[PDB]
Amino acid sequence: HWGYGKHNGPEHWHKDFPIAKGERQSPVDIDTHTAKYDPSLKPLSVSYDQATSLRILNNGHAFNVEFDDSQDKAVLKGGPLDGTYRLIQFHFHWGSLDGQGSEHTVDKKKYAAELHLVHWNTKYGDFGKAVQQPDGLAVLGIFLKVGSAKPGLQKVVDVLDSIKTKGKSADFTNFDPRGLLPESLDYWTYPGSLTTPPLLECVTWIVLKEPISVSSEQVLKFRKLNFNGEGEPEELMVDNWRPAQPLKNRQIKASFK
Ligand SMILES: Clc1ccccc1OCc1nnn[nH]1
Ligand SMILES: Clc1ccccc1OCc1nnn[nH]1
Ligand SMILES: [Zn+2]
Image (cartoon, rainbow, N blue to C red; front, side):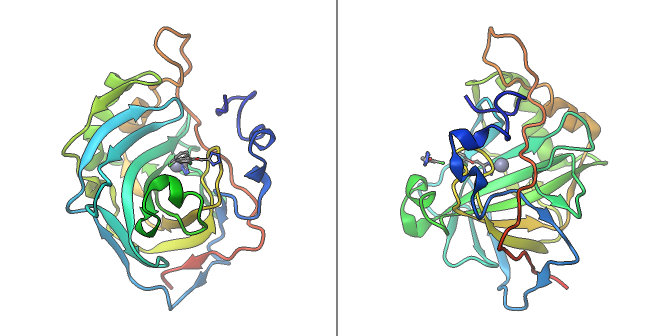
């Protein structure tokens, strides 16, 4: 029954998921003056040419666009990563207002939203095995600011009225996630966690410095989604973000000077 409300939100999670107060929780604030450029980071490789999207699902917390990850079709390699990480899904976190919504922050700045492209390390064979490993997942995180429309997002926003409530899904084939990327792949990286229960400490976070711009109209439509199921009282799907957690004994590394 976790969620994002007063009674079941991030401040409550620790009672069922005590790793909420662990040593490598996400998100974090990225202090741009303290992150250190790491000249040994190898180049980042985003290889999504063969991506095979399947379905879009409202899971009660966000909406997920799922991919076929039964072979190496859309993968992330390089950067801080060893080996090959297969794309399984992407989703977003967003706010009730344009001044909040991202999970990560940059010198305490909140963006309107944050895109997470979730990938798992193919040496562990499946996603469920990978989340039990400290290097099991790699999440590519992309900030959204409100400005000009992002054309490569519009197919997503146009299908949202078909998955308004919890447990609704729709066909979502032939979607190319390359349309969601900014021009630059300059990034920050640190070891962290899932940002929702079960908050497992299994994620290499790779957060792009360059946000994408989306229109007010596009993000307005995210906010028309519902956390509730059909035939239940309406609760708008807004503010599905966890606030920044203590950095503890971690260093954030930059790919760029
Ligand atoms: Cl996150 C997850 C993905 C797939 C299968 C199981 C998963 O969580 C397992 C779990 N739940 N509580 N601790 N580990
Ligand atoms: Cl990807 C996933 C599967 C099961 C439970 C939670 C999951 O992701 C949580 C997360 N981490 N960063 N954003 N969402
Ligand atoms: Zn996420």
